[PDB]
Image: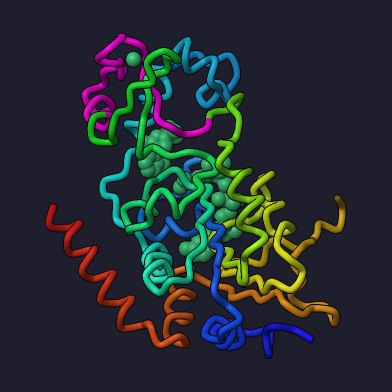
């Protein structure tokens, strides 16, 4: 009946190395970056505490946002074992797409390219002048220098405010999300959900966009995605369970176990160690 021979990580690895599994979509959240030192990120006289992340207030008073940005700026941008496992998926020719709710750029530092990524909530990687007639793009280095010097970032062409490409409250989701969703989920063979509680919509509903036969593996500290008894959910434990698997623990250790099952543990170790060595050497 089912594509997985058993509702275990071993069954998922066997399915992955079968000829049936060619296209893997990753859905990742804050949990895949806590081991990197980036925790769950989410005087100025704010009218309401959400104003610091609402677009209108930012364009009126951006200084609070950038003060918070200096306070939260990471001491290092070192992706995790999980990030590099996704890079390995890319190298092995199995990665259809990575949908991320994170803005910390670690997916790109790990070697995932823009075509590989749907950054559902944007990113700090790129910033743009807020003027529609200009839209000058600035890199993260420029923005970091502005934030650390405590100088509000202004466009060099038109002197307008420059905003990191994260999706503020009152901004729309990137259209790439919907277009890529409509195409990708016709093609997915395996859904790999890592480090997210699947509570924020519409990113959570993504799991219901997979075909009914598509196996779905959750690597997370706690079970998530099951239908809420109060209000296509994950079914790990019922007698009708057939495709959903939960590996409970650190995302790094779950990806290590999966790589070991796949025979990739040495490749993953070498990749992580060389990339971390190059980051430390900057
Ligand atoms: N780094 C970031 O970019 C970041 C951080 C915090 C919040 N957010 C915002 O939160 C929203 C998305 O929510 P979400 O689902 O990503 O977060 P969430 O807090 O709802 O879920 C994260 C999940 O990961 C688990 N987890 C944490 N550390 C883990 C680890 N080391 N190993 C395994 N599991 C671990 C947590 O227990 C939790 O179940 C977006 O609005 C996003 O902008 C982003
Ligand atoms: C500097 N900064 N500022 C914010 C905000 F103000 F929007 F919350 C988020 C971040 C940021 C940037 C890069 C990596 C990780 C994070 C989140 O810890
Ligand atoms: Zn400009």
Q: Residue 280, percent across and down?
A: 17, 58
In the shown orientation, is residue 241 left or right of residue 216? right
- Magenta range is 143-167
Q: Nearer the viewer, residue 31 or 189?
A: 189
Q: Nearer the viewer, residue 190 or 56?
A: 190
Which residue reaches farthest left?
281
Q: Is residue 25 above or below residue 183?
A: below
Q: Residue 142, percent across and down?
A: 23, 29
Q: Residue 69, percent across and down?
A: 37, 31
Q: Is residue 70 visible?
A: yes
Q: Is residue 60 above or below residue 92?
A: above
Q: Is residue 72 visible?
A: no
Q: Is residue 236 above or below residue 116?
A: below
Q: Quadrant of the N terminus?
A: bottom right
Look at 38% across and 25% down and name the residue there.
128
Q: How is the image coloured?
A: rainbow
Q: How many marks?
A: 0
Look at 53% across and 28% down and name the residue there.
168
Q: Quadrant of residue 194?
A: bottom right
Look at 58% across and 73% down and name the residue there.
248
Look at 58% across and 14% down and name the residue there.
47
Q: Nearer the viewer, residue 121 or 70?
A: 121
In the shown orientation, is residue 83 left or right of residue 4? left
């Amino acid at each position: 009946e089912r594509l997985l021979d058993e509702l275990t990580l071993e069954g998922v690895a066997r399915y992955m190395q079968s000829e049936r599994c060619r296209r893997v979509i990753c859905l990742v959240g804050a949990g895949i970056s806590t081991s990197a030192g980036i925790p769950d990120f989410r005087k100025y006289h704010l009218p309401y505490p959400e104003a610091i992340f609402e677009i209108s207030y930012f364009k009126k008073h951006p200084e609070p946002f950038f003060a918070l940005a200096k306070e939260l700026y990471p001491g290092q941008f070192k992706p995790t074992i999980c990030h590099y496992f996704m890079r390995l998926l890319k190298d092995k020719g199995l990665l259809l797409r990575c949908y991320t709710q994170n803005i910390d750029t670690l997916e790109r530092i790990a070697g995932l390219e823009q075509e590989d990524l749907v950054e559902a909530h944007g990113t700090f990687y790129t910033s743009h002048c807020v003027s529609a007639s200009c839209r000058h793009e600035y890199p993260l280095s420029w923005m970091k220098e502005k934030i650390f010097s405590e100088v509000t970032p202004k466009c060099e062409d038109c002197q307008s405010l420059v905003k990191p490409d994260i999706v503020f409250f009152g901004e729309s989701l990137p259209a790439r999300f919907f277009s890529c969703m409509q195409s990708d989920f016709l093609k997915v063979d395996l859904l790999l959900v890592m480090g997210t509680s699947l509570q924020v919509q519409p990113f959570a509903s993504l799991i219901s966009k997979a075909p009914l036969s598509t196996p779905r593996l959750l690597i997370n500290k706690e079970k998530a995605g099951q239908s809420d008894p109060f209000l296509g959910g994950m079914d790990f434990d019922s007698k009708k369970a057939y495709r959903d698997v939960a590996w409970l623990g650190e995302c790094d250790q779950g990806c290590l176990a999966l790589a070991e099952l796949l025979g990739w543990k040495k490749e993953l170790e070498d990749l992580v160690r060389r990339e971390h060595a190059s980051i430390d050497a900057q």
